[PDB]
Image (cartoon, rainbow, N blue to C red; front, side, top):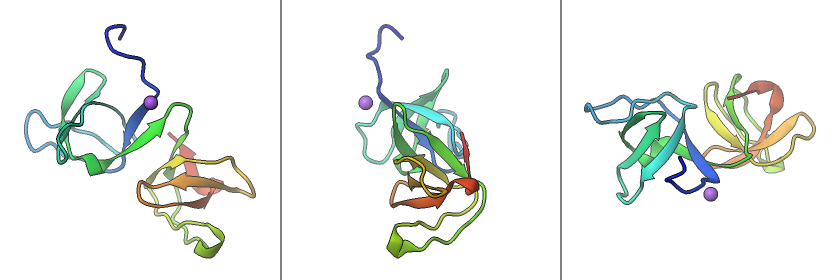
Length: 123
Ligand code: NA
């Protein structure tokens, strides 16, 4: 809104979170989340449209404006020493480089590496 400050980043869900309580933020992998309270280490408050609630912070990944987000469509074991990464189908990742050689650099939230573009879909 115009009352809030302009935002150059957001977050995307990495996993399914099932609400424990009426005020937990239900979400599926890939949904865009605006974090409105991250002052508590173990439980953040976020919004998905008009939905608002609490959720575990390790269930989301940070995305900068202009970064592309993908879902893995095919599990694939990468050659780690040359910079590739192993990912499983339905995993959510953030793009961190330009495509080259049929691979693109992505971030899982804990590891970085090259993954085949044919085994990703944009979300
Ligand atoms: Na920002």
